[PDB]
């Protein structure tokens, strides 16, 4: 799977995109963290399906797949949200039936809303494309946990870096395909990758909130993630 | 005007701007135990030199003093950390906080382990000094740029300048790799590998800031006014 062309990498990633879920609230009746949590919990299931279709990810051990998802899942929900929200200045499209502005985020929620809104606006300014977005989301999946991991290990990390390298090649191909000069290409690569630092930052701040709730299962456990990932072949 | 430096001149400027390597102040003839005290004293002295360094990052002092403070308030711990990871590079398994304070993980350990992993990543990539100073400057310019939370005309001008300087550092990084003979493909791949490590350095800073805030001591986190005073 390290033998896909750049164009096939793109097709594969676009094909793998999760569905856009709806919030579950009675639209005929007049809670917020409740809605957001229910949404995130349903997305996680589809996120696992998506991860398994990221070329190269299922070549890893089960344990390493879990570790990467444990590190990246909130960043992945967040970049998804920021992407969806790109065409709604000043609002966050949590779901097509749950479009919130910052005053609807108002304890310690408006702080993270604002960061998400800033990132969406940055995406809008850069005119981020769908093909670029799916590359970036895959990069988060592969990179966020890689510094936190034996001979098999070295083989695992080497493979992860090879896949990351091929996504870089793909991003560059997309930019060359759109007519950017070599200078513009490396400049845009750099701009896009630096935004991943801010997405990390946001995830840390959000994780900080979810832990402060002290509810038994508000961070996906290793064993929960393993259960979702450790699929069987009887379907 | 420093948007008109050559890449070589950018590198020369950054290398010359490098802060000194400070020493820990413990009495070496006395015994050992303390640790957070030593680490804090070191960081507090480094911060002053950090401000001097920042003012020499081409393009930084063209910003308003308010924006200079905002960038440094965002980035200061990331900058201390990338500095640490860099001078620790040739000490596998240890962190060279200062030449007289080289610590292993047994001597927080959550944070030590992340820093040690980054040092090893730098070692694995054979990070060069010229690359290091570009990355450190990128942290300074990038870390706070999405939290300005103001869109006055001046702020728009500020963000544009920050991104033009960041673009120039990118050009400089690519120029360094071209000069070492890397192919175009290798150049782009290495640029990406280096920038993705910045995400981990952000992560570490957040984990570290969580620690310093949990201490509940009056000024462990540098206040806006303190940075303002140092940058005046
Ligand atoms: C992995 C699941 C198992 C237990 N679940 C706990 C609920 O965690 C979350 C995660 C994200 C969110 C909010 C959200 C919901 C859907 C989405 O597509 C993106 C986001 C972005 C973050 C957002 C949030 C996170 C933390 C505090 C406030 C808001 C809220 C609660 C997470
Ligand atoms: C801005 C200064 C004013 C008040 N100071 C509070 C002390 O903050 C720190 C910052 C970093 C450190 C440790 C350190 C010291 C020197 C250095 O060159 C790099 C580092 C990397 C982080 C390290 C640390 C940070 C947080 C918890 C444990 C260890 C310890 C205390 C910070």
Image: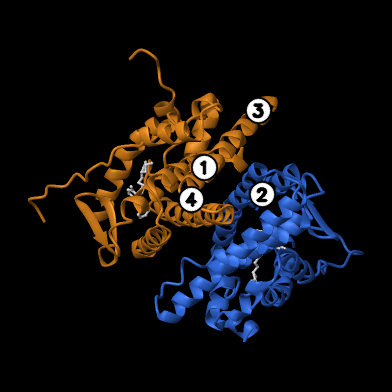
Chain colours: A orange, B blue
As drawn, the residue found furthest toward the left would be A28
Q: Which residue in the protein does label 3 denote?
A: A155
User: Residue A173: which numbered mark, if any?
Assistant: 1
Residue B181 visible at all = yes
Mark sitting earlier along the chain (4/1): 1
As drawn, the residue found furthest toward the right would be B29
Whether callout 1 and callout 3 share a subunit is answered yes
SS type, badge 2: helix
As drawn, the residue found furthest toward the top would be A234
Residue A214 placement, left or right of B38: left
Mark 4 packing: few (<14 Cα in 10 Å), some, or many (20+)?
Answer: few
In the rendered image of this protein, does residue A152 appear above or below residue B90? above
Residue B212 visible at all = no
User: Residue B136: which numbered mark, if any?
Assistant: none
- Which chain is indicated by disc 1? A
Residues under labels 4 and 3: Cα distance?
36 Å
SS type, badge 3: helix
In the rendered image of this protein, does residue B12 appear above or below residue B176? below
Residues under labels 2 and 3: Cα distance?
26 Å
Q: Give the image quarter of residue A115.
A: bottom left
Residues under labels 2 and 4: Cα distance?
48 Å
Q: Which residue in the protein does label 2 denote?
A: B109
Whether callout 2 and callout 4 share a subunit is answered no
Q: Give the image quarter of residue B210.
A: bottom right
Mark 2 packing: few (<14 Cα in 10 Å), some, or many (20+)?
Answer: few
The reply to whether dot 2 and dot 3 touch (C-beta < 8 Å) is no
The reply to whether dot 2 and dot 1 touch (C-beta < 8 Å) is no
Residue B191: horizontal and vertical position, in percent? 63, 50
Residue at image location 11% in from the left, 50% down from the top: A27
- Which chain is indicated by disc 4? A
Mark sitting earlier along the chain (1/3): 3
Residue at image location 38% in from the left, 30% down from the top: A49
């Amino acid at each position: 799977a390290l033998s896909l062309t750049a164009d096939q990498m793109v097709s594969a990633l676009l094909d793998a995109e999760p569905p856009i879920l709806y919030s579950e609230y009675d639209p005929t009746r007049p809670s917020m963290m409740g809605l957001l949590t229910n949404l995130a919990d349903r997305e996680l299931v589809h996120m696992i399906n998506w991860a398994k279709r990221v070329p190269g990810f299922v070549d890893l051990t089960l344990h390493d797949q879990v570790h990467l998802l444990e590190s990246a899942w909130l960043e992945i929900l967040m970049i998804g949200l920021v992407w969806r929200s790109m065409e709604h200045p000043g609002k966050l499209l949590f779901a097509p039936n749950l479009l919130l502005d910052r005053n609807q985020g108002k304890e310690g929620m408006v702080e993270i809303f604002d960061m998400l809104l800033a990132t969406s606006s940055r995406f809008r300014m850069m005119n981020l494309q769908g093909e670029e977005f799916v590359c970036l989301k895959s990069i988060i999946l592969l990179n966020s946990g890689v510094y936190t991991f034996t001979l098999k290990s070295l083989e695992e990390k080497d493979h992860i870096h090879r896949v990351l390298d091929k996504i870089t090649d793909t991003l560059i191909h997309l930019m060359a395909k759109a007519g950017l000069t070599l200078q513009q290409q490396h400049q845009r690569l750099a701009q896009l990758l630096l935004i991943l630092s801010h997405i990390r930052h946001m995830s840390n701040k959000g994780m900080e909130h979810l832990y402060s709730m002290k509810s038994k299962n508000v961070v996906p456990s290793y064993d929960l993630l393993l259960e979702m990932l450790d699929a069987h072949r009887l379907h």
